[PDB]
Image 1 (cartoon, each protein chain N blue to C red):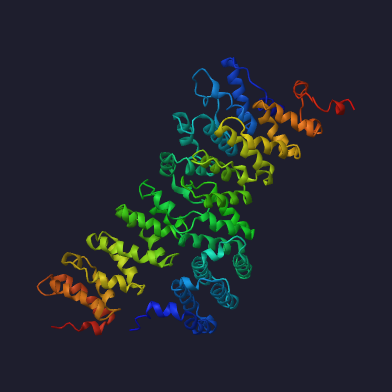
Image 2: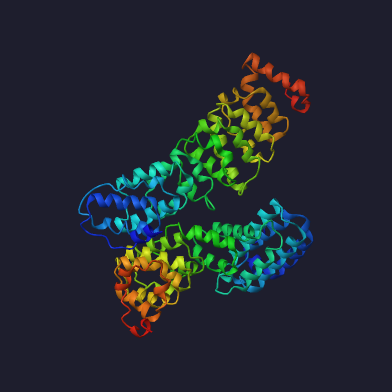
Length: 306
Length: 307
């Protein structure tokens, strides 16, 4: 109680030995408070000598309120800038504690220093979780860049709207091998509606055009999930219209029928590019398809005997 | 086959057209989606020459009936948000005057049927600003939303104003609006952003004429001085001295927190005037070491200390 007041209010001697200076610094490092912090800044503006202050001023050991008040009143008086020493502090403390980063985002959203915000999210993205009223416009411009490997592998840990604007980045970054490896946490988004049924249709457009040229694995897992929600005609009838020969020869027989059987004339024009594989095409592909029509009894679609 | 009706006719006999539409929705309250898109389109086509108080209150009186028969359910709530936000957006200047009878009376009806009143009013504001993205500044919209005293609108205002970077071209009309928000929800981060703003200004505007800091709590008044004096000129400008000379002598809590700063900054007359106007300060100070009192010479009021 006496120390916080003496140190935060007595005028300091402009001749103070290095031996005294280290002692004064250790007092503030034990009783971190508004005035004991402030009067320790009102000295540094006048030092006719070098020395990093952090080697005796272990702000990474301080409580979060004191760390915040320290950086605020440091930067405001010194140069409104981040010198080297201040970067090396921040890159060890904020990745070790999300609570510490909370009031710290405001000051970085003000004076920008964009390269700092890139490094914390690149060490761990679970920082985006507990943000006050987080929005699009912002998160779309905070492209995570940390490989989509972290974001798709945890997509369920977001909110609602953020699911749409995440997949909007995965596509526009060509992150193919991240929509695939985590497909099961993605199907449950397009299923559950959203804050904008409009962004769904444009996302579904960006999916089919890349799937047609790149079967990989989700061509089956996706196109199955498409027809279990017949609220997709504005994409199925396009998919059957944009067809190319080698694309059809990778359609699973369990799926080519489950597309056309729960449909009529519109999806039916897909048959145009199936003639290439029945007539003069492939011996065993015709026979794997012929199982499915007989086992389920899909007779109205059997009208193809010429 | 029904290829709409030409835009002239809709604008012309609008007041005849909408009679039947209102009566259809007053019976169709059973079908949420039917009532929802009818309102959205009738507003999206509502002509400028009809953007008055009568047509405004009519849509409010329609939504009232629909909402009182139903209940807060996820499906009902999120459509109701998009409907009501489009209604306020269509009439926006008629809700954004400075007293707005329509604004406040509307909130007192929506609070009747929700899982939390403080989500319904807030998610309203968040949709309205997602519509108005270049026509109307957030400040003017927030200026009237805080006249509700809705504690969840205050929370989001502190989160925005304390952290969004401000435009170096801001009209005086925006500047006064942003200032009035801080005069209702003053907080550490909201003050710190306004300073990083004034440091980048092209115009002088002696700030105190808009800030009214002597109305803010003791912590708010303290923290404002610390960052302002240091970022500005390491000293006080006219209005600060005239402020401090009459806020401090009447409040001992504020005096106790500012006393160390005024001491380390050598502000002699500032300290002396407080003792000359209020001698009781010297016995409410914790740890008045005899060296401090020998340097806080009473000067005037010698006729008080011996007495």
